[PDB]
Image (cartoon, rainbow, N blue to C red; front, top):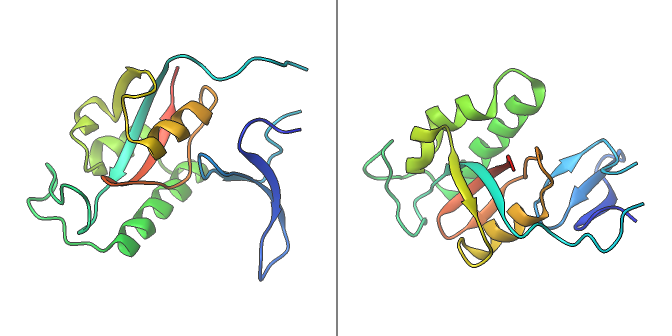
Amino acid sequence: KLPPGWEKRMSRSSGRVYYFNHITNASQWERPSGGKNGQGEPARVRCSHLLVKHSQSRRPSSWRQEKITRTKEEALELINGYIQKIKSGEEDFESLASQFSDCSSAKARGDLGAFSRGQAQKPFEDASFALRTGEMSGPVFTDSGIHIILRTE
């Protein structure tokens, strides 16, 4: 049971049950499903993303800063912060992407438009196609940096 990638897990050093997606790295308290079969994955998806780059990114530069110097660890902290802010309701994904994404797609509020498999880096692609419409990923690591991905179509 559960849709692709999803497993019921428990927090360590704690003990709360939650649900984790091994492909998108999403975590949530809510069971991800409440009978459709042979549905497979979509042939095309549209996504927005918020990218946080770090010193080890394939291109450690962005419209936000000539030279990205933050560490991968510091980038992950930022990503975790943005996810928390979006889930709390204090911020919205598009506003954060417009302001803080290291990708040039910040100018389109994070929107990358529609794409097919073979078009993006593997971890980004796998996460995007494993998201259902309206879902947000957890931290997704690629050679570019660390992404939060929102599937819009």
